[PDB]
Image (cartoon, rainbow over all chains, first blue to last red):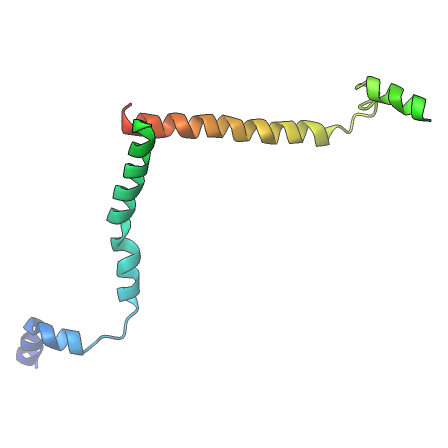
Length: 51
Length: 51
């Protein structure tokens, strides 16, 4: 069983096609778009700084 | 009565003879605090872009 679990742990496809039920994926976008949010708002402050 | 109410118009004290004046002072404070923060928001956004 430990051997099987290790083999499945290394298998990325098995993780993709098993244990997929959590809602964390939705939250990953909420957190990742923070870089876009920084570049855009810093750019808008820059438009004001120039004008 | 119109004449007396004109005399009311002339005197502001005659409007706050009874000291329940929270209305006017609170309105003025709200507007001025919005000004204080608005001047500060432009000033703080300026410190972040340059210091």
